[PDB]
Image: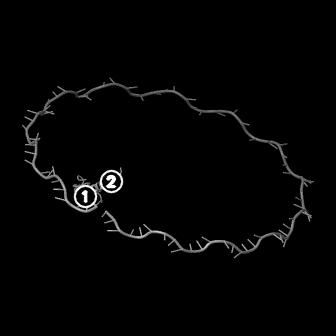
Amino acid sequence: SAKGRAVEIISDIGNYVEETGMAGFFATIRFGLETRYPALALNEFQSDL
RNA sequence: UUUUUUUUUUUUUUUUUUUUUUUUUUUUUUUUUUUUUUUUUUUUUUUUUUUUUUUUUUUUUUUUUUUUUUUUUUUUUUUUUUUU
């Protein structure tokens, strides 16, 4: 549907609001899991994976 | 969050050549001449029964062992702090 000025501002703010308070998990995903490093498969990370 | 750039400027008709000139009948050879019946051998002559052996004599029950003896709850950690 069409978005008014208030709704557009609210959605733009919610862009920042999303995934708040969970920086540890998403940082773990993005950095440790993605960006595949030869040090990942090291037999002390399999349970964490 | 965002901070640049993002019209155009040339060329682009044509000019040659492009009929033909030779040759292109024929001339040999092309019947036949030998040989072509037959003459040996071609029955048979040994051997060809048989002569051993062929029952049996051992052994053949059994003698062990065969319950059990431990251990077997628990004692950590486990929200969040950036940017966008």
Answer with mark 1 or mark 2, whichever residue precedes in sequence: 2
Image coordinates of residue A9 in percent, x first then y, are 29, 56
Q: Residue at point 23% right, 55% down? A: A20
In the depicted structure, whether residue A4 falls above or below residue B18 = above
| Other-residue count near label 2 (Cα within 10 Å), few / some / many at <14 / 14–19 / ≥20 | few
Image coordinates of residue B22 in percent, x first then y, are 85, 70
The residue nearer to you, when weighing B19 against B56, is B19
> Left or right: B34 with respect to A3?
right
Q: Residue at point 23% right, 57% down? A: A23
Q: Amino acid at mark 2?
A: Gly
Please indicate, yes or no, whether residue A6 appears anywhere in the rendered image.
Answer: yes
Q: Chain of mark 1?
A: A
Q: Amino acid at mark 1?
A: Ala
Cβ–Cβ under 8 Å for marks 1 and 2: no
Alpha carbons under labels 1 and 2: distance apart: 34 Å
Image coordinates of residue B69 in percent, x first then y, are 7, 38
Image coordinates of residue B24 in percent, x first then y, are 87, 65
The quarter of the displayed image where residue B46 is located: top right
The quarter of the displayed image where residue B2 is located: bottom left
According to the image, label 2 marks what residue?
Answer: A4
Number of residue marks? 2
Q: Chain of mark 2?
A: A
Please indicate, yes or no, whether residue A40 appears anywhere in the rendered image.
Answer: no
In the depicted structure, whether residue A43 falls above or below residue B66 = below
Q: Which mark is residue A11?
A: none
Secondary element at image label 1:
helix
Q: Residue at point 25% right, 58% down? A: A27
According to the image, label 1 marks what residue?
Answer: A27
> Left or right: A35 with respect to B65?
right
Secondary element at image label 2:
loop
> Left or right: A13 with respect to B20?
left
